[PDB]
Amino acid sequence: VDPDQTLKACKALLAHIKKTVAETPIWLTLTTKKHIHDSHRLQPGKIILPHPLNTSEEISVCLITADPQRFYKNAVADEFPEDLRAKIGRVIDISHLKAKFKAYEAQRKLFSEHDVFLADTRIINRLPKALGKTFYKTTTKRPIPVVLMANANARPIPEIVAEIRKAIGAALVHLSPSTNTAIKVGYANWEPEKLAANIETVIRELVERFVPQKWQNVRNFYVKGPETAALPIYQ
Amino acid sequence: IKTYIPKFEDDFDPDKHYDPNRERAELAKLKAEHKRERKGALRELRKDAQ
Amino acid sequence: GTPWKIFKNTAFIKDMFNSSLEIAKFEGAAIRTVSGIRGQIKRALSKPE
Amino acid sequence: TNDLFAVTAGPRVEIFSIRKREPLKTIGRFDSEAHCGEIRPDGRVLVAGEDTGRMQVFDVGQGTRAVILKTWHIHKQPVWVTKWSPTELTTLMSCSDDKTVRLWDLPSNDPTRLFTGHTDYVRCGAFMPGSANSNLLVSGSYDETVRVWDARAPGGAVMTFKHADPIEDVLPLPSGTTLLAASGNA
Amino acid sequence: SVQAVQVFGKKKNATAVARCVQGKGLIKVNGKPLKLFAPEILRAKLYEPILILGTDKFADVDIRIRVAGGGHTSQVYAVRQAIAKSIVAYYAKYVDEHSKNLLKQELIQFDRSLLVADPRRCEPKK
Amino acid sequence: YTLLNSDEHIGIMRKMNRDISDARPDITHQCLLTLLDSPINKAGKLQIYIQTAKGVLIEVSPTVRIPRTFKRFAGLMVQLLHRLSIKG
Amino acid sequence: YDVLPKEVLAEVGSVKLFNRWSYDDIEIRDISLTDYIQIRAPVYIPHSAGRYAVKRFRKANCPIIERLTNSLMMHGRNNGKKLMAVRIVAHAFE
Amino acid sequence: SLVSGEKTNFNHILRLLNTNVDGKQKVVYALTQIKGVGRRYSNLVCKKADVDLKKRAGELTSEELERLVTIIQNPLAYKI
RNA sequence: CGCGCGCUACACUGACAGAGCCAGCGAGUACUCCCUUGGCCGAGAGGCCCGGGUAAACUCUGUCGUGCUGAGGAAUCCCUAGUAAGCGCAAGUCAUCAGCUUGCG
């Protein structure tokens, strides 16, 4: 697959969107040809983008840890003041989440409060039934994996902050048992060269990491906007 | 003492709502008459069913 | 029609009538399942018309 | 033994710790000023008189506690000092801006005794420490007078000393016999 | 071979097992200490049997309590009943009956509900 | 809807033969006018209640200035007796 | 000590209300109310689950701070709450 | 007999953009008094201008007062 | 249109942020809140993907301070111990009951 087709298609698509003011996400729709069965392939992943997805001007992260919440809150009070303490408004363990936040109004207030979410890989299995469907199933604001894994068994704190810096702007990947998925690459206010770079590295990482029996199982990637038509890419 | 003026309607009756805006008063009157007619229709239909 | 919420016996049934006037006409009627379960229309439901 | 001392500056007092020397609590309930932040010999209760004339007495714990016990608004003109009695726990004194010093008791809503006789601002005063000097009060004014009163007879001053300068500070000596009046350049 | 006494305690729906063995003097409720498990004002309800009997009686025993059910108040009353009945039953079995009778007399003179749970039946004025 | 006075209901109460002198709201009106214009009300040391024959007990705020005319006063008193309050 | 904090182990000597206030020297000034103001059996906190409303004059035996607490929980929104009332009594006595 | 009362005149009514009445309350409770300004909005204004929440209104210099009157005109020029 | 019976709103018994800690009844291969803008694979009917509309309470610690941000008249009725009152959780049993009913703590 050559990226010149992606560049001409995404330029035509931005012209199609235009002809604040845009503020629409652009994604590519993955199709595969065989059903997906492995529950370890059904795990949500992240793809680190070369141009990060988030603006990081005023957005607030929420960080969901597992075992002692006081240890992780003291690490947040310890480590890094420039980028991290302005963003990390809450550190919630999964026990405190399942305790305090079971109500529809409470999880609606949390979803309206915070801007983007991060969780640990031992918790995102638990999270679609801890956090509500109005948090999880509806929109893109849903937790991204951050590997806080080696008194809690935790990775060392500079690697923790490096992982959170990598994972704030990363692109979330959900897989589904069906054969069609879609994955966001950016917005419509961006430049199409950056868009085509994001689509290229997402194609590389999506196939060669997540879709099993990789380029055998691949089907068409159709670049799409919110309400527009889809443009081909590797039929 | 800073005295104040008692707000009251001169020709008072309990049988009439008081509202400045005729649009809002008329919309509330139409909603009340629609509820009354719907309840009367449901009562007549239920007695005919029994 | 189609069931909407199903309790032990009383089920709420959705895609059959259009208004509470029509339900009040067909109050007490012998409703039936495809399976063979008999039943009776009891009361119109307020919030979904 | 305790680890509390209070410094008032502007519209708030700030109870400091002795060991840590940090501002342990900052109390800014006052409307306008706070002219002496004086805590009781028990060490749980702070009195402070404002610039609007009220004095507020409020409990502080070891931590962040500012629960208001009583408020008096009888002076109606500023109160510059308000001091606890060194022996009794509920008796306190007040030198206000007008002409008056006066004795209060904490349960009552009335000043228990009133002492007049000064002709200018009275702004410094203390009780007299001693076994024999149970109820004597000294206060100096801005009228260049130090007066010491018996609290048993609320007439005039028992003794009066006239200086040459506006009298800024007063302290008795712990033997109870002698007294230092700080007035001007001497 | 080991000296061990298991005693139950009861309130509305809050029940407490207290196992009392020969020990150094600790009291644990749900694996946490007795000075931790309660609301902050009902710890004086928990410390009632210890302060009645004195600490010299509890110097030799180790009590482990589990509680389930009820609310905070019912669980606190169940814990204090399990504590009092537990030390009385240990002194029944493993030291003298005169000490058992002295402990029972002091606890009954303070409050009978430390030993005998009185359920609230329904019998109003018939 | 108007208060029961001796102005226009003199025929009704004289026909039904029950104490034409009793139904007088003008006493309450002139006395409440007196008390609201008095300087002890303007200083603020006056508090005024009305008890009617029906058992109705009305507190009148000192901060009110009543209608000085009996027609507006009767309409205001009817609205008070039916809505249990008069907002400013 | 079994498990006791320092304030309780300090005032381990006698029965003290809220672990701070003694019942030793308390004199009821009126002769008529010595029967009905019950300070004879001391209590630690007023929260005592006692059936003091079974029959007549049984409320003449419950301690007077429990009466003060149970009458503090008196309006429409303070009805069930007893820890609020014993906390109000503790703060008021301090 | 000469101590500087350069700060003791602070409990007076200050004037601002729209309201002519803004006395001493605090620094964030004084911002609520201006119409259209909220209780959660007033804390965002103070963290940009390096003014402390501990101070009152009237404890600010003639430079520090006007810094909150520019930033109340344009909330977009300072990032939000 | 009238009448009550429930439900809701109406501020010191306050709001915000934290920390900690408590139930009982409940398991029929059975349960799902709508309807839609687009696109995938669909000769056609559909299935997908992405958008739009185990408690409450309680306890402890801090941050701010009465600010359309106002607890119900005459009457009339009911109520004496786990009773009045507050609170949530669950079920929906051939009659009644989802605008709610009945349990349970």
Image (cartoon, rainbow, N blue to C red):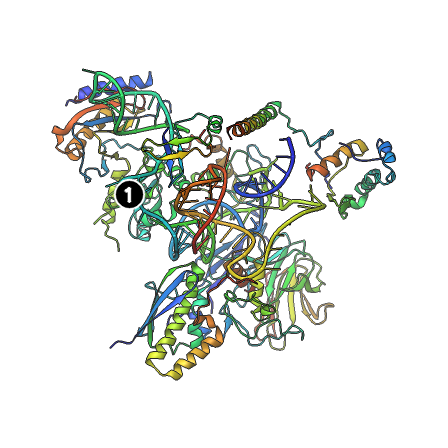
Pinpoint the chain carrying mark 1: A
Q: Amino acid at mark 1?
A: Ala
Instruction: Identify the residue at image location x=34%, y=46%.
Output: A91
How crowded pointer 1 is (Cα within 10 Å; few <14, some 14-19, many 20+) is rated as many
If the image is split into quadrants, where does the N terminus of chain C sit? top left
Residue G89 found in image quarter: bottom right
Q: Position of residue G72 (x, y in %)?
A: 58, 59
Question: Which residue is disc 1 drawn over?
Answer: A119
In front of the other: A40 or F43: A40
Q: On the picture, is A81 further left or further right than H38? A: left
If the image is split into quadrants, where does the C terminus of chain C sit? top left
In front of the other: D127 or A89: A89
Query: Tag 1, which secondary structure?
Result: strand
Q: Is residue G47 above or below residue G40?
A: above
Q: Position of residue A234 (x, y in %)?
A: 16, 22
Q: Position of residue I7 (x, y in %)?
A: 52, 42
Q: On the picture, is I62 further left or further right than I44? A: right
Q: Is residue D10 in view?
A: no
Residue A64 found in image quarter: top left
Instruction: Identify the residue at image location x=43%, y=33%.
Output: C41
